[PDB]
Structures are given as C-alpha cells and as structure tokens.
Amino acid sequence: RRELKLLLLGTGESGKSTFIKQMRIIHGSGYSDEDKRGFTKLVYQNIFTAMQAMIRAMDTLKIPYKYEHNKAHAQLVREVDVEKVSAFDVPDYAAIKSLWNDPGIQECYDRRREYQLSDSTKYYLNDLDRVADPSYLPTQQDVLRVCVPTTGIIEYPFDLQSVIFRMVDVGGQRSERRKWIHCFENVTSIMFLVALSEYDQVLVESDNENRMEESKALFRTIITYPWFQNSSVILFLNKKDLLEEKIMYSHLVDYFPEYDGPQRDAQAAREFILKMFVDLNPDSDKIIYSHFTCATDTENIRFVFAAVKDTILQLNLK
Amino acid sequence: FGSPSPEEAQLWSEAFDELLASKYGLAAFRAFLKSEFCEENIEFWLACEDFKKTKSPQKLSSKARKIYTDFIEKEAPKEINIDFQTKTLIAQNIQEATSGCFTTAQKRVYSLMENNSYPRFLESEFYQDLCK
Ligand SMILES: Nc1nc2c(ncn2[C@@H]2O[C@H](COP(=O)(O)OP(=O)(O)O)[C@@H](O)[C@H]2O)c(=O)[nH]1
Ligand code: ALF
Ligand SMILES: [Cl-]
Ligand SMILES: [Cl-]
Ligand SMILES: [Co+2]
Ligand SMILES: [Co+2]
Image (tube, rainbow over all chains, first blue to last red; front, side, top):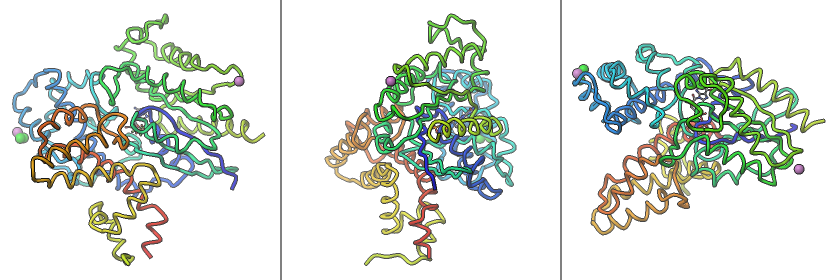
C-alpha cells in the first residue's frame, strides 16, 4: 500500500467525472451488464432536460416551430417532472421525436453555443429509438455520455500494479471552488481538464463571460499555489472530438483575436490553445506535461493513462 | 436510543424516499454528505420542504429572504450548485414570495442528490455495515 494522491481539477463539465468513469473501466470496479441498468433512468432524465432546454431557447431566441402542433407537444414536454420519470411513454416519445425532427428545433439546436445544453444531446436524440425500446440496455458508451453534475469532493481510489492512485473528483462550478481547499494537502499531481470545445460558449454561473477565459484564469491560479510547487501539473485538452466538429463553422479568431493561424483547422487551433495555457506559467523550472483527449473514448484514454502512469511514477518514485 | 434494524436500513436502497422517511437514515445521509462537503444540498432541500408549507405572508416573505442569502446569493456561505437562470428566476420572485418560489431549484437539488450522493451513500462502508 504505497499511496499517491491525484487531483482532477477543471471548470464545470470539462470532463472530470467522465475521467473517473474511464478509470473504473480501465483499472477498476468495471460496469457489469447489470451495473449499466442503474443509469437508464438518468439517460431518460438527460433526454427530457435537453429538450426542455431547447424549448426555452425557442422562446428565448424567438425561433418559431415549423409545425404548430409541436407547440402543444413542447407544452407537454415543458411540464414533465424529470425526477418522477422512470419509464419512457409512447406519448412522450411521440412528443420528443416530433420536436427533435422539427426544423425550428433543429435551427435552435444549431445555436446551442448561445445556451445551456449538454454536449450529449445529439448522441441520445438520434438513437432515441434504441433508448425508447421497452427492453433498453444502455451501452457502456451510453454511460460515459451521461451528464451528472458533481457536487463537493469525492475520493476514487484505484490500485494499479505497483501503486494505489487516489483520485479526487470535485465540483467544477464557481460555487464549488471554495470547497477545493479541503483536498489540497499531500498532492503528488494535478490533472487539469479543459474542454477544447468551450472556446465559444459562455458560463452557466453567469451571463456573458467566456468559458475558456475562465479556464485560463483558473489554471493560472492553481499553478500559482505554493503548496503545489512540488506537484506535477498535467494539462488535458479534452473534448478534442467536439473540437473537430466546432472549428468548421465557429471561428476561434473572433473569440481570441490573437490567433494568427488559419481557420477551419482542428489541429492548428488546439496547438494554439495549448500554447495559451503553457504561457500562463510563471515558474521556468516547472515543466507542464500535456495531452489532447476525448474522455468518452476508452481506447484513447488507455494510451494516455498508461502514459501518464509512467510520467507520474518517474517523477514521484525515482 | 434511535437505532434501525438491518432489514429497516436495507429498505433505504429501494429508493431515495425510503431513506428520507427514516429519521435515522436521514441523520446518516447528512453525515455522509458532510464527509464529501455537499451537505448544503440536503439542508437547502429541507429548508424548502418547510418553506413550501409556510402560511402567513410575513413568514412567507422573511423565510424567502433567509433561504436566498444562505444558498442563492453568489458567494453565499451555503451556495448550492445551480444555474444563473434559476438563481435569477428566484431573485425576482422573492419580493412577493409564494410557496412555489424555490420549488424549481428544490427539484434539481433532489435530482442532484438522487443521482449522485445517494448511490455513493449506498456503496459506503457505514451503510453496508448498517445492513447486517
Ligand atoms: N463528445 C464528448 N463528450 C464528452 C467528452 N468528455 C466529456 N464529455 C461529456 O460532457 C459532459 C461532461 O462530463 P463530466 O465528466 O460530467 O464533466 P465534469 O462536470 O467536469 O465532471 C458529459 O455529458 C460527458 O459525457 C469528450 O471528450 N467528448
Ligand atoms: F460541471 Al461538473 F462535475 F464540474 F458536472
Ligand atoms: Cl399530443
Ligand atoms: Cl401526439
Ligand atoms: Co399531438
Ligand atoms: Co522555481
């Protein structure tokens, strides 16, 4: 029992809990055929929430539904107790299906950068048939995609061959950052997640404040902490897949006018993103290890967390 | 006294309400949430469950303020993890607060425990020992 503690820090929804999920899959408790059943209800809740979100965006943005009966459908969806949902109704299936395929909702969906909408919305609504089946088992990939806010501070210990890594999931939101104090003692390494896809969104916690400008801000502060001078700092530029979608119509240059590189390139964009973060470092002797990740892909993570194992060992063993 | 039988405590697995029904079960779950620094969700929910039942438009307006400051106002001592939307939705409603002022946020916070802290309570050693 040689134990090393690791902090998963990052703003809201950078993909911290998803990482923990992937730990459990690669080196841990496993998600049994049964285990999976437990999530169903939340996948349902996610679906309803996302649609409830898009219906407000229709009001908010004054986007009209193409088919007028979709309003009374949206009315029905409006008024669902999302917690009391346990089964998936045929009327509610009809209502959502109908809405999702309304071109007004689709227009509203296109403009999700202008509002709060889970990144997993499309993944679920397109496989709504598969979900709505009365004998529905969620895949493991379904589970990773689920959006469940983390509140407070939770220790998730995993025994790798040589060592027991003690991982700590925290709340990404402003409200939770005052709590992070409670897990700062005795830290071998920070693992700071950043949603790459966040360069054009605004913050859930406040109106009209750029999400990436937040992360830079936070990263700098964390780095700056003196009780972290002997901790290894590993940066994860996450949601790289969502970046490959996003950069082909939302132009980084309009949010970060520094960017002298070309448009419509995932790579050249993200290399710039990385530079931005590395530059926030004051300490010249402190070297900042990084990675580009998609947290919802297990085969990808394994070549990172096998790699990051090797890094953290070499640092804080020999 | 106050102790629950193992059978009694096993029932708390059925659903989140079987736990909350239990006076002790509640005490244990709070203790748990303290251990992970998010007891503010359960206090707030409890705070709402009383407010909901408040009668006189005096208390219905001065409790309205008590809750807001404790949980909603930014940098509030017990600030709960919720959206600027919902928080503002409340802010405005508080001048002439009715029973259904926080009930939006109450529901989210419940779901936020239901789907998160509650499962973990169940996988805790304190609980599993209690089911013996
Ligand atoms: N497409 C995609 N979705 C992701 C990725 N990482 C996380 N997500 C999703 O984005 C949401 C954020 O995950 P979560 O771990 O809850 O973020 P946290 O709040 O910081 O823990 C979840 O719905 C995840 O399924 C990614 O690399 N690609
Ligand atoms: F925003 Al999080 F866990 F930090 F869902
Ligand atoms: Cl209908
Ligand atoms: Cl219908
Ligand atoms: Co109809
Ligand atoms: Co130095």
